[PDB]
Image (cartoon, rainbow, N blue to C red):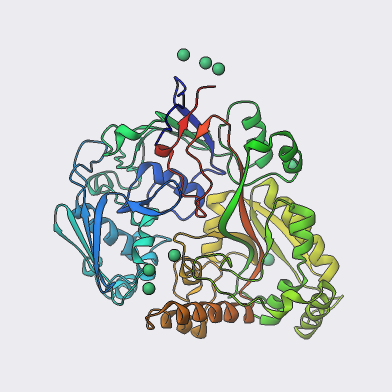
Amino acid sequence: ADVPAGVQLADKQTLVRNNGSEVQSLDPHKIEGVPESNVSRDLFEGLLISDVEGHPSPGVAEKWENKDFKVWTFHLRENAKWSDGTPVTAHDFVYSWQRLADPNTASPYASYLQYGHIANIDDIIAGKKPATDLGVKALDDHTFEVTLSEPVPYFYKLLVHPSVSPVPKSAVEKFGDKWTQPANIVTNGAYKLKNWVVNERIVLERNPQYWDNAKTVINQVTYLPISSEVTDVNRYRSGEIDMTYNNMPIELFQKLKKEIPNEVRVDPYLCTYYYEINNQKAPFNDVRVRTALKLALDRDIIVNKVKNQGDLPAYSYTPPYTDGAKLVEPEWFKWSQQKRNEEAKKLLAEAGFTADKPLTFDLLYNTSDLHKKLAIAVASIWKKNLGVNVNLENQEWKTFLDTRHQGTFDVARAGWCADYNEPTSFLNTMLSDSSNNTAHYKSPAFDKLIADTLKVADDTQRSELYAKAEQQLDKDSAIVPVYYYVNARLVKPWVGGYTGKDPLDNIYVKNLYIIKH
Ligand SMILES: [U]
Ligand SMILES: [U]
Ligand SMILES: [U]
Ligand SMILES: [U]
Ligand SMILES: [U]
Ligand SMILES: [U]
Ligand SMILES: [U]
Ligand SMILES: [U]
């Protein structure tokens, strides 16, 4: 943390953050969500980290070079250490990236190594080559070299993500899936795990071995698993919580803007809220059904009437303000809602649906007052506008993600937030073989458009190709875009170091500080 001259620090440097839900895991290779990544950034540090404004910056790697954007060489700082005092080496990164690639690990982020195009990843994921053939090597203890199969100019931007953080081989091998228990875990970020009580709290304490420990200010941070946004706000206002999770309750938000304006932080965020359709399950394998659902949802009602927290109605998957996004707003988005409704009804009528045999299906969402209220509104809108019946189902976060991966669903609420600020951070998740493809969408045409983006060596052709890839997804109605999120949360006046300038919201508790109050 960089405490401004003149600021008086509180005697007790502790923080309590709400984290939305119980985490899937603390193992960097078994996680895929925001709550998971929030804790992961305090515990495991990769090659690069985001600074306080979100810029990719030195993590374990103090400096790096690239040759033709294909061979990346990272020079690891000599004093990088794990919490048990042992050095973090390039060998840790080699083991870690191989474990991520290995199909036996079954990481939801196995495809992150395909997104960066590390050599031999496709064959490794497919079981054709052993994970040890991955294009990574330790040239020495302090030098990690990555070899890609094609030039990727934005490659280093990927490296702040939890999936490419190092994990400690000896703990993994000795304790297997209990390696992340407090008595066994070993970490290399600014914090160490002190306590983990499922559905109660995660307590982290400062890691004295961290290389940049002298600049850490907060001594302990607690992450809570509260999925009710109302309850989060209540425990924030009671004094327990210093920073709410960044999901805000429809019940109270308008009142909060008037009551504590200075604490209501609202900043740009590269995330899209959408209804994920299971594209491989009848009748959602019919483009007419998906298109009907996409058109009949009234975003103006949802975004401006129901939620009204500053979100913008969405017509694409990639947020339009992602760096490199130059998207074409589809003609249906300019139509009137009535015109969208007629087209929708026409398509469903063409798909075989009638008043006597209507379309009925489930709408799965992770427990939350916000998603429940939005799903109830969407259900009402779809019933009224298109004559469809939906059965709402809530599931806790970890179960909910497993259901979407399993494909044991019809339509699910969804939100994707960028991992690096570039259109492929979104677009790569709709690749037929992506480990992040919970839409179960498989388009050879879409796949080809993205493969072509690194076959050209310039940004304008690349941006036009991303635009076309979005048009292909839209043409297929793979999803139902709802809104682009804003990052809205409450932060007490005494929490310093949180700018709100990072559109990825990659917060590190090592950058924060408690102002005397
Ligand atoms: U004190
Ligand atoms: U105090
Ligand atoms: U660049
Ligand atoms: U950029
Ligand atoms: U269903
Ligand atoms: U509620
Ligand atoms: U470039
Ligand atoms: U105080």
Question: Where does the image place residue 497, in percent across and percent down from the top left?
Answer: 47, 38
Q: Kindly identify the residue that appears in the image at 75 percent across and 67 percent down.
A: 297
Q: In this view, does 107 lie to the left or right of 134?
A: right
How far across and down, in percent of the image, does residue 490 sit?
Answer: 61, 39
Of 487 and 104, the residue lying toward us: 487
Of residues 186 and 474, the one nearer the viewer is 474
Q: Which residue is drawn at 75% across and 37% down?
A: 258
Q: Is residue 142 shown above or below 259? A: below
> In the figure, is residue 89 to the left or right of 96?
left
| Quadrant of the rendering where the C terminus is positioned | top right
Circle count: 0
Residue 177 placed where, x, y %?
35, 47
28 to the left or right of 61: right
12 up-or-down from 164: above or below: above
Q: Nearer the viewer, residue 152 or 404?
A: 152
User: Can residue 134 be seen in this snapshot?
Assistant: no
Which image quadrant shows ligand 8?
top right
In the picture, which quadrant includes the N terminus?
top left
Residue 373 appears at what percent x and percent y?
A: 74, 51
Residue visible at 26% across and 74% down in the picture: 68
Residue closest to the far front: 6
| Visible residue check, residue 467 | yes
